Image (cartoon, rainbow, N blue to C red):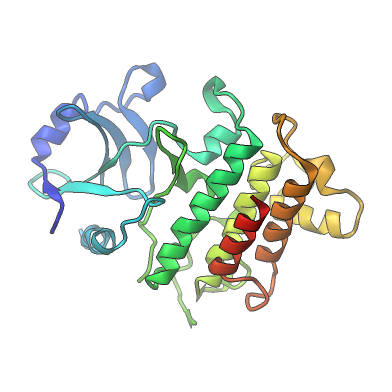
Length: 279
């Protein structure tokens, strides 16, 4: 396939022997993604992301061959020869939306203007996936990466599938649709999850917080409906460009996305339209 074949020993070499120490401390580890660890490598004149993990390996190189879009992380290549399997991706220097919202490591808070762009970018990514009959199954802010220009790139396609039910229920609890928690498999569940993402974008809050009432961000939608609070009271304080009307428009998209009944939710195409209007 169109992907560059890598020697395991080159990948081992360019990652400082798969240095397990985190980046912030001088090592090469960038994260752990269930099916293995992700390392920074310096190959040629290029920083890359190497996942060091067989069945669910050849699935990815299948999906990734077909699924290339401006708002999806691109696979560059792979390693099959001896010791461990490796997947190599384009490196995203601004990390995840999760971390930028939490301003992890002292990064500056994001403007409302950039947040609108990232939201649109991510809706474009999902639309492509759905257009080509793929369900992501794990849409969340930690799986939205950001490149040099803060362009949104959807990653972690491990659980991606090319309405039926399953026994192996997967996804992240705080972002999962009611039906998806019942083993149902459907794009309508990606929308529910994107809805939680928009709530994170508006409020800068984590999807779950055990010391918080409510623990689940999605439960604020009911506090607003029961007008015991308003969206205004929830808006991230760490912005200076957030006009009330556009924020309200995004909250409306989130609200619709979070319809607990799967058929009443808008599809990704409508979500896309609504986010352009907002802008």
